[PDB]
Every structure is written in C-alpha cells, then in structure tokens.
Length: 72
Length: 72
Image (cartoon, rainbow over all chains, first blue to last red; front, side, top):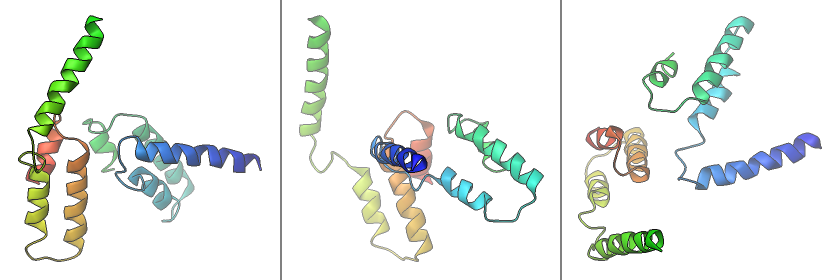
C-alpha cells in the first residue's frame, strides 16, 4: 500500500510531466529502462548500464556529452 | 507600474501580430504536413515523418535543432 501511494504520486507527475510542454513520447529514456531489463544481460554489465543511464538522465539533452551517452 | 505596463504592451503587440496572421501566418507546419500527406507513402516513414513533425511542433525557434529537424 505504501508503494501504491507512491506510484499514485508519480502518476500525477506523469500527468503534469506530459502536459507541461507537450509529450515527446512514452519518454524514450523509459523505453531504454524497460529494454535494459529485457535483453540478457550479465549482472556487472547491467549495473554499468544502469549507472550510465542515470548519468544520462540528469544532464540536459542536446549536450554533446549526451549524444555520446545515448549512442553507447 | 512600469513592469506591468511593459508586460501588457509586450503581449498586446504580439497578439496583434498573431491576429495580423491568418492561416497561422505563413504556417510552414501545415505546409510540410500537406507536403507529407499528398505523396507516396510507406508506413514506417509515416511514423518517422510524424514524429519529426511533432518535434518541430514543440520548439519553434532559438535552437539550431528546430531548423535541423525541419531540413531533416
């Protein structure tokens, strides 16, 4: 039930996050987060990929740093 | 008083320019939509064309990337 309350909270963040500037998509970073936990993968490289994803998530997009971390 | 005057006159003139605009002004958005919908066309490139159109619909000017997605 505590997770229920939390996931409602972030459902509301879904709503305003969507409508606050238009919706690019299901948030293709969230598509990457889904796909990482589908294909394979070994445990060490899954940890490395999730740290790389969280690093890409909190930087501003369109940076030349970000277009390398997405291609990787 | 001067700040409130500035904001009112600023968006007044911009609304004047919008009204002096019919059919979204020149409105290259609907022009490239008509340039999509009247030729071809396959189906995955339909999705690619509509997502590039939706990336053009959100941001309008200031970044190089808006004109990049226009040309692309």
